Image 1 (cartoon, protein in one colour):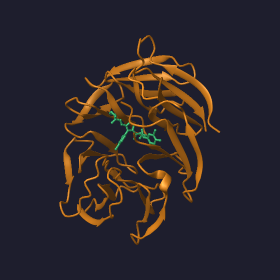
Image 2: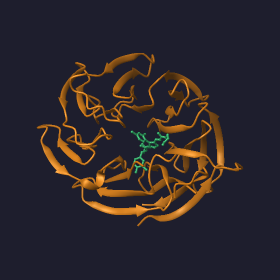
Image 3: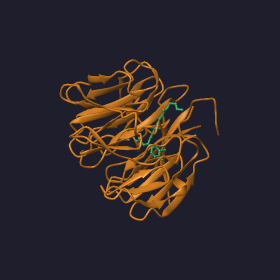
Image 4: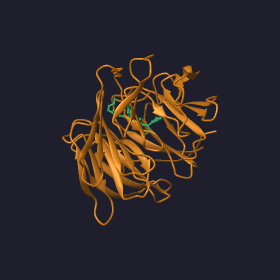
Amino acid sequence: AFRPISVFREANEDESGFTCCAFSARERFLMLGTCTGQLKLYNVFSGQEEASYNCHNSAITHLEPSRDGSLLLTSATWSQPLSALWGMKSVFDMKHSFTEDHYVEFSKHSQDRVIGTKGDIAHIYDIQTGNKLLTLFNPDLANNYKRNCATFNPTDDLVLNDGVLWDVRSAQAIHKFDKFNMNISGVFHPNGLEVIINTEIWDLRTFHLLHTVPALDQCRVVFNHTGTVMYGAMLQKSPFGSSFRTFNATDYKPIATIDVKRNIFDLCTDTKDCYLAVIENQMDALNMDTVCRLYEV
Ligand SMILES: COCCNC(=O)/C=C/c1[nH]cc(C(=O)N[C@@H](CC(N)=O)c2ccc(F)c(Cl)c2)c1-c1ccc(Cl)cc1F
């Protein structure tokens, strides 16, 4: 099941403004972005705030800590810069920013690069210098996905941008996956063998269609750290509707559908994959008053 374990809100605020979340390196501590552009650290069990840092002058949409705990990526709604990289050792400080990229992710195997998305375009940056190494856009192969989000594969040698597979080393598009939907651009399966683009599962080796999974339509997906479970939530204000779905990552078979009966802002699992944190708005409320709910997987 998904048994509720605890709940908390942005402490001492009339309107709680949590917008996104990620577990930190420290087991019991969750990092939350807020609609006023702050980063908060909370104890997930006590529900108490520990620390607060100022990141952006607009709502944080998404954040990602590095695995080693030294770095954090944030993205905001209408700030300049839209995304930034923060150092978290010694003092919390901005290292580099990515002016117009509305989404950013670390590379996966070695976290020495950032990949940012601006519309149909990907930008790769060096973490050391902040320098833009590559711009990935091919007018002949573009799918023009409206919710494109560029990403590295597990070994960092490939990028998926706008449904196009790029070889990072040569900076060449090697394959365009055919377009089946208007919005979702896709992700790599952590197994390194498959690419999941909306409802279509493609083989990375042959570029053959392996499976169709209709329940993934319009979903953002995240895997548990172990790579055994895939979580998906349909995009619908709140980025998501009121439900998320789980699937077996080995065979794409549905496990569970959870309707939390409130709009979802974000979802994450801890490094040990024991707990799920979900940001939920207290259907289609104009009032912003989010809680973080912790669930047992
Ligand atoms: C109208 O909204 C105004 C402005 N707000 C936004 O834009 C907000 C954007 C935004 N928030 C969270 C995400 C996101 O993708 N979260 C990932 C998990 C993660 N943290 O990686 C995710 C995966 C599976 C799930 F089941 C759930 Cl519920 C969440 C996203 C998100 C949504 C769409 C895209 Cl293309 C990229 C994104 F990062």
